[PDB]
Image 1: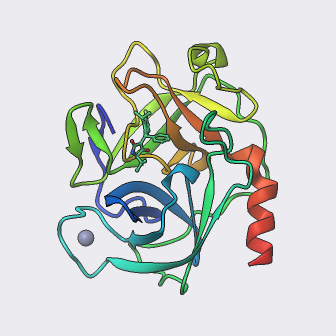
Image 2 (image 1 turned 135 degrees about the vertical axis):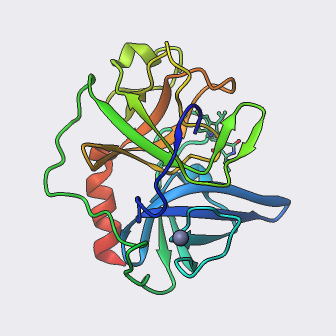
Length: 226
Ligand SMILES: CC(C)c1c([C@@H](C2=C(O)[C@@H](C(C)C)NC2=O)c2ccccc2)[nH]c2ccc(F)cc12
Ligand SMILES: [Zn+2]
């Protein structure tokens, strides 16, 4: 998160910190959010050979009783995810066991309605990602308020599409999500409407988020079958 504030500790109890293992490199990191006691939603590009989820964290360098380090048994990447266009950048992780409900750990379930969210309003995103182009990931959970933009604002991303994705962040400000924040939720009036996907390498906003409403049928299909 660039240009944000430190979250009040444990104030976003659905937030998940992902450590991703691959065969031929060191650990990589993403965000995510708990939508059922045994399911975390995140980005498809955060997939790997294996993943560990930490719930209940604020400062990710300091072990505490709120932590739950949970095993992932299976990864469900969207079947149409495309590594060139980055369309359909969404994935569900099934946990080996159901998480414990505490003050610091709880689900963010979707409401019944899945209305298409138009441009104009302010939304909030949180993560442990880089705080600048040349700065490491944050030790503490950070968050920032961003403007939902008209789709033409993201035209320079040649594979952006308005039906699939949200365009997020006023170009006149530095405020943005960045590397390490991918997979985290964008909340508009307390309701998850987007998932951090990608942006420019120089972190100039706006950035591109997966539009959750488009994928509600697919999410439901996976949850009901597993
Ligand atoms: C384009 C790039 C600057 C970028 C990324 C990267 C990236 C991650 O997400 C992590 C992952 C693989 C552990 N390491 C990376 O290099 C990316 C995105 C999509 C596909 C592959 C890689 N994420 C962003 C999030 C917000 C943003 F504004 C920009 C970016
Ligand atoms: Zn604590």
